[PDB]
Image (tube, rainbow, N blue to C red; front, side, top):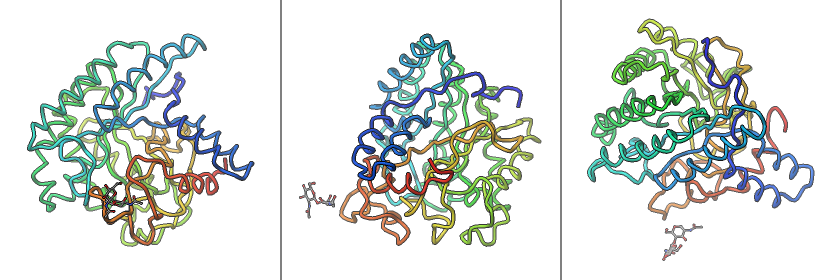
Length: 358
Ligand SMILES: *[C@@H]1O[C@H](CO)[C@@H](O[C@@H]2O[C@H](CO)[C@@H](O)[C@H](O)[C@H]2NC(C)=O)[C@H](O)[C@H]1NC(C)=O
């Protein structure tokens, strides 16, 4: 499109991820690998606002970005993930979301959005790009047979709508999460997905700030695979470019000339999964293509690193109340600590296996 949110901006580098990376790098014993690991702190990632407790951090990042821009003559851009739906992750065996539909989820989520908007409103010289609710709308395409998802459908739609409508009022550029090629990219899922995303876009007023969709968030697919990963058999859309090329024209027909961003933060190593749906701490993952607007596609505004590499996707300990058995599969790195906590061995392998190399 004419307006790529990243062009002309300096991306703000997360100091939190930077702090995690710095602490991790000093524990890597091989000196050459340690220096490569430390440099990961210079690679832009998205900040996950996975609870209300993260909102004060957002405020600090906006204010810091505003000052860094003035100190360097740059316009700064802060990258965030909106990730706090009530009954979050409806199809997962376990979820860490703090809100529940049964306990005023809609009002609590609205207040979470209001607090985020109130921060963003104070720093108008900082641009914000937001990924909207990973692991939400995609469940409403394929997983309505999951009772928790069926029962969450109206709340997910209302809450996502509230986020889109209100973040647009402060000029946030937004990409709705849209799963990945092995979820919504199956040819038979493309039209139901397009119909749902279009309805969501319409309900939020077709705001020009709703730029399009984010794909492969927290996943491992290639953007453009050298050859199809065996997990993809049966799906001609075996990588993200095939998925996006197939979905984008369906959105165009609705009047939404959508553009896309694609997570490649853990895509450096292909052919590491037994089944396509295995998502938790996949063993042998490597850092992938660094964020760039040089995407190879008319539809793709940026390759991005949405999910921060090194933060555990979930514990492998079956005695934890947050245990999801996906995290103990044979292709999941184990033992793995609780979701969000640092997984040092996994980070070291992400560095060692990076492709392109760091
Ligand atoms: C695996 O999960 C279990 C349950 O969460 C953990 O065992 C408990 O740990 C807490 C303190 O961390 C104690 O209050 C409980 O009494 C423990 N229960 C038992 C049966 O030991 C266990 O620590 C976890 N293991 C790892 C490596 O995280």
